[PDB]
Image (cartoon, rainbow, N blue to C red; front, side):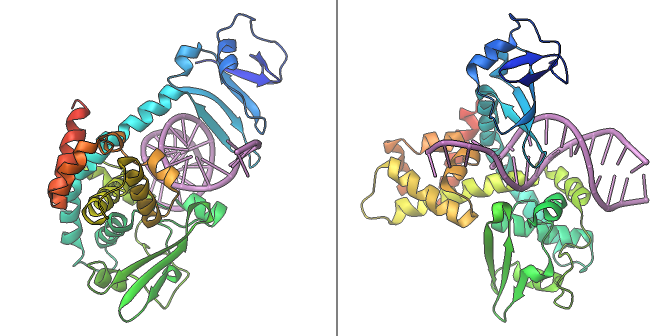
Amino acid sequence: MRALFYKDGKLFTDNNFLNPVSDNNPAYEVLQHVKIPTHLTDVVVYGQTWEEALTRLIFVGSDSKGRRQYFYGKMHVQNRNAKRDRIFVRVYNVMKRINSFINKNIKKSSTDSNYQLAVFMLMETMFFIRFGKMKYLKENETVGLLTLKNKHIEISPDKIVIKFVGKDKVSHEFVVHKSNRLYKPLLKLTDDSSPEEFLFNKLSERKVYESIKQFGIRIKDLRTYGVNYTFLYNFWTNVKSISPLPSPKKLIALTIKQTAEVVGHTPSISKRAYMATTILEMVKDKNFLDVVSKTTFDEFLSIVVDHVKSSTDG
DNA sequence: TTGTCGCCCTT
DNA sequence: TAATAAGGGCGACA
């Protein structure tokens, strides 16, 4: 994986474009098959044959913020997507332990890291909010879970509203009713009398990483799971409620819309970067809608988990 | 003795 | 559209 430097359709071994590579160099095969976007500068193209480019990183260049941007081949992306099946199943098998951890700690002291993590984990499994790295709060004013501040928590005598601007300037509103098990512990954690402070003031990126490590997943996996679970809940409800029934094609489209709105991102992004491919393939089958119809949601969730488990050949 | 930071990869 | 932005995860650094 030698680094080669790109400039105006031709390739060099040199930082400042003296000394061009060989004419027959395999990298030129790659350049026939991909277009370097012209908004980039300092473009590096990796010397390899097209067939190997397919499978991994292809080139990287700097956008106008000065950020390094990374471009991958179609096989790399395919493997990426194929992983969502296993993640969905993986999270599903640790939910019982996650809840167990949550409920052990939510009766604890207000400034206990474990109590704070418990709440963190319960907001996450409830609303699928992104991790919220400090970095993006400084750079872009983006708030996610870890970067939530007391000003983002509005208290009413019957509900708590969490309101904040997340990724891509998208505005989010989540609501916690009195009956919700998040009410009591969230009201206890937040301090009205200092709005400029972080909600999870005893946590940090490192604390979260260490804590989640025990379930063998990453916070983003909780979000990937939440999107699939919500899809399944809506799909199940839709089949269960909607006048005779539309085509599976349109039933998936509706379920994806509903799910995307709950989660708060576009339908296209939901289908493409979140949904387990097997679920998407499984639900197309018309005969399968008979199966769904006669089930409680729990036995439905199980059928899907099982099929994804074993169609994944594991 | 821990809060940034770069690199890679994801959305 | 057609052009191409901004998130997370992990480990090194002082």
